[PDB]
Amino acid sequence: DFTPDTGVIAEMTGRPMRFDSDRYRPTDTYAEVACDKVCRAYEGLGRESLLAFLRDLTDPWGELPVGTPPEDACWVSIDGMPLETSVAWAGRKAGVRLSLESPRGPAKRRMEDGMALTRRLAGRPGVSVDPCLRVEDLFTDDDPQGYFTIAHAVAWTPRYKIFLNPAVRGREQAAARTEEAMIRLGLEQPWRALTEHLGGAYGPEHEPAALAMDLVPGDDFRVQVYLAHSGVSAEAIDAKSAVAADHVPGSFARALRGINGADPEWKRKPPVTAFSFGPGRAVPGATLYVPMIPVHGSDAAARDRVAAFLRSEGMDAVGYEAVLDAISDRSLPESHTQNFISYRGGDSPRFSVYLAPGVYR
Ligand SMILES: CC(C)[C@H]1C(=O)N[C@H](CO)Cc2c[nH]c3cccc(c23)N1C
Ligand SMILES: CC(C)=CCSP(=O)(O)OP(=O)(O)O
Image (cartoon, rainbow, N blue to C red):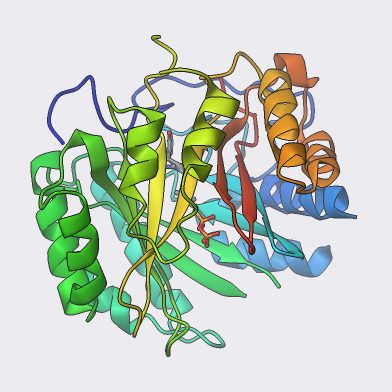
C-alpha cells in the first residue's frame, strides 16, 4: 500500500485504445456486445429479453457504439471495455455473470454513474442497497483517485453486487476505510480475526484493493475484501488464508505454483485473495485469484495450464474450455482476454474465469 512497483496494475486505464474486433461492427452498442458475450457464455455451458434487460441495466451508455473507444478505459475489463463476462462453477452449479462500469468520464462522473445505478437497483426484486448506502461515503469523493470507484455485477440463476475502491483517496488509507466499513456493517469480529491473523497491519503484502458486497438483505448478505499480494511467495500467500473457515492447507500454494510457476516483469500483476464475510460468521472464507493475462503469453497457454490444474483437482476442464471457445473472438494463441481465474478447493470446490470482450487494444 505504498510504492508504484506494488499493488494492482492499471491494465488499460490511462492508455489510448483502438477498436479491433473480428466479431463486432463499430456500430454495435455496448449493450449488444454484452448481450452477445453473455449468450455465448451460456452456449459454452450448453435473447431479446436479455438485450432489453442489459440496455436497461447499462442505460444510458449502453447505447453508445463500441467502435468509439472511451476517453478513459474502464478497469472492469483488462481491454478497457465497460463490461467483463465471467463464468463460475461452484460444486455442481455453473452460471454466468457480467460486471459493468460506466465508460463515461471523467472519474467523478463515472463514479456518479455508478452511484446512480445503485439507486436504480434499489427497488428491484430481492435487492437491498441499505448496507451499500451505509458505507458509500467511505468510497466516494469529489476527486477520486485510483483505477476505479464503482462497478457492479449481475448474476443470473437476478442478484447484484457492487465493487468499491478503498484506495479512492490513496492506498495509504485503504485499510482504514475498509476497517471502518466493516465495523459499520457489523462485521468487526471476523475483520479483527483476519487483521490479527495477518499481523495487525495491512501493507502491499496483503493490500485492500477492493470491497464488494452482495446487494441483498438477511443472512445471505455477503461482503468480500480483496487483498492483493505483492512481493510474497505462494507459501506465504497460502499461510495468509489459514484463518479462513474453508481453508485447505497448501491448496492455494499448489494452484499458484502449478498454474503460474515460481515468483519476472510479467508477473507484476499480483495474485489476490478474496476474503468473504457474512452475518454471524466469526471468520471469513477465502478464495484465490490467479492472474492470467499477462503472466501467461496467451489465452491458449493459460488455458492449457488451467485445464491441467482443473483435471488434477477432478474438476470440469471440458466446461472451462467450451466456455473459452464459445465466447472468444480470436484464435486462442493470439487471444489475450483472460484477466484472472478464481479457485477454492476442498469438498465444495469453486472455479471461475473472468473474460475481457477482447475488442479494444
Ligand atoms: C481488485 C481485484 C478484485 C482485481 C485485481 O486485483 N485486478 C484486476 C485488474 O488486473 C481488476 C479486475 C477487473 N475485473 C476483475 C475480475 C476479477 C478479479 C479482478 C478484476 N481482480 C482480482
Ligand atoms: C468483477 C470483479 C472486480 C470481481 C468479481 S469476483 P466474484 O464476483 O466472482 O465473487 P463471487 O463469485 O460472487 O463469490
